[PDB]
Image (tube, rainbow over all chains, first blue to last red; front, side, top):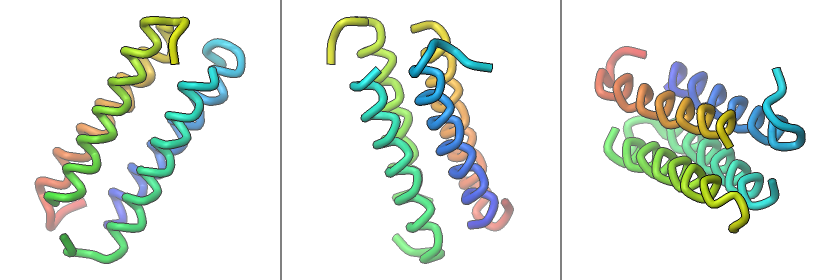
Length: 28
Length: 28
Length: 28
Length: 28
């Protein structure tokens, strides 16, 4: 459970980063 | 944006549904 | 594992579908 | 495309890494 909860939370955060990037181009 | 944005939000919701599944532990 | 593996496989499949839709640039 | 494309491929690979981790079952 706990390690997969961390990895899935990292997926939501990377998928949110692509929303942030699409609102301009490729933000870093 | 809008099409990819809706689908990225769907990926977050499926990944969050996966968090809710793991919390049952050793289920289906 | 088995259902979680199927859910994660569907994330790869939807995420790959967004590559296909991005390649058109002007489709939804 | 190219940035979002690279980053969706990073989602596929992080989701695939989760399959490889789930195959241990008793560890992480």
